[PDB]
Length: 196
Length: 196
Image (cartoon, rainbow over the protein chains, first blue to last red):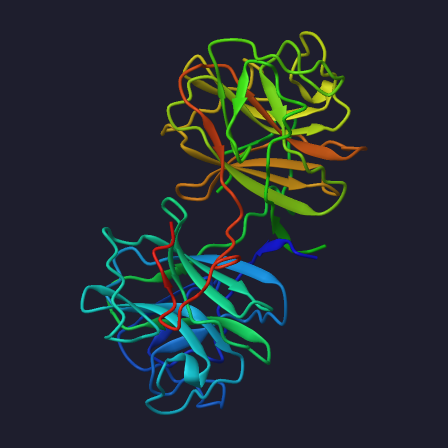
């Protein structure tokens, strides 16, 4: 009904700019040392170093969490599933992108230089919040679950997807899997202790 | 279903032991210096300093996060709606309690001295995860989202509720509200910034 979903987000290799290298579990990405031999399929970002989450939301409330520790240049947010991928695209609401980025050591709303977020501190884990019907894309510091930014209310119209950009060469972006408990694992007599 | 519910947990004042002091919003609680004049009612813990979440779960996957910073004696987890409220009840699976506790500077699963969890760090934010159909009650350290413990799988049989015990009169426990983005707040055309 009106439940918040803690979404499980896996990256889509068919959308990934060729400089982006996906982990084997597809839950993390790093900008690697060249341009992989990947087809220029129409869902692939060919210029902007971007990748989408595979999952798409068409209603209700969803959030997921992104680890960005030791990444200089990154973008997180939501996009229309059908946004333009090809050429020097503007990552702004008008083209169906709702984003937070780190650029020149600052936090910037809607990939804009006229929107600095004067955060007192460094973000390690970012929460990306979507209320589909409310037109709401919001961002959180998951250190203390403090609000960072809500994008201007937009009607989404079509399904939306998790959006990512990795500018820097420096460290991976990790998408935090949704908690699963012991799902699919043996729980012995004393319980399952410190699973990894 | 298949999706993880980020539950919004508010404490039920009718369950709360008389030495428990709830916040106005009922989203935090402390053990106070005296017994409050609260109606007797069958739902009230009368001997153990416990309180339940208002909402019960009969199906699906749910989780919520609890802040226990500077709380020396605490229990979090899940219990059957119908657990014994009156008298000294052992907080064990047999009596419908699935818990993690801090006790004598030690972490113990199932309120048992034979279930000591050898953690390297002091817990501050604890995730409580429920998979009703799987019989799964799991605990997470929400600093790094790392697994602490899954109880031996149990047939819940009846609806279950968030369970809390607060033994020490030092610090409140806080139940982290579900993220809501800009719900009930005007988003300016500039978008909403560091909401507090």
